[PDB]
Length: 185
Ligand SMILES: CN(C)C(=O)c1ccc2c(c1)CCCN2
Image (tube, rainbow, N blue to C red; front, side, top):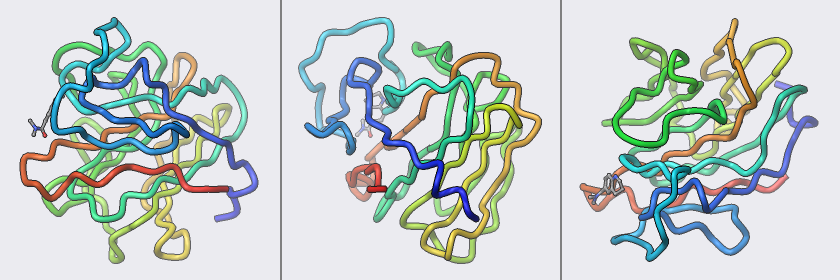
C-alpha cells in the first residue's frame, strides 16, 4: 500500500479509558493494570472491557496510523463512532458503530456480525489502519509482512465523527500484560 503519506499523530484520551488502564505520559501507550487505577467514574469510560479512544475526531479525509501489538494474546483495533455505547455489554459490529479486527485464542477475525475469519500467514507485530471517510472505507495492513492487506470494510455507514478505537484485552492468562503502542511516523 501507499497510504503512509496520510499519517496522523494519534494520542489516547484518558477520560474515555476503562478505570483499570494505564496510559503513558506521552499518551501513546496503554496497558492493563493489575487493579483500579484510582480515577473517578464518568459517563465516557468504557465500563465492561479494557477499551480506550483516541482524542482525535475525524469527519472527512484520509487518515493512517500504526499500532504495535508485540507479544499480546488478545486485542481489538480500529475506529468507532464518537457516539458508541460505553456502559454494559455489546458486540463490536458496524451496526453498533465499530469497524475493527481482533486477535482472540490464536485466531484473527474482523468485527462483522457475525465475525469473519482472517487469513494471516505472518502473525503481525504492527498493524496499519487506514480510513477514507468520503469513500466509506476502513482497511487494515500487516506491517510485519511488507504492508500486506488484512481486511477492508467498504460501504461503511459512519453516521458521525470517528475516533481511533483500542482494546488491550483481558489478562486472565498472565500472558497478555503487554501494551498497545502507537508507532512513530
Ligand atoms: C480480571 N482480569 C484479570 C482481567 O483481565 C479483566 C477483564 C475484563 C475487565 C477487567 C479486567 C477490568 C475492567 C473491565 N473489564
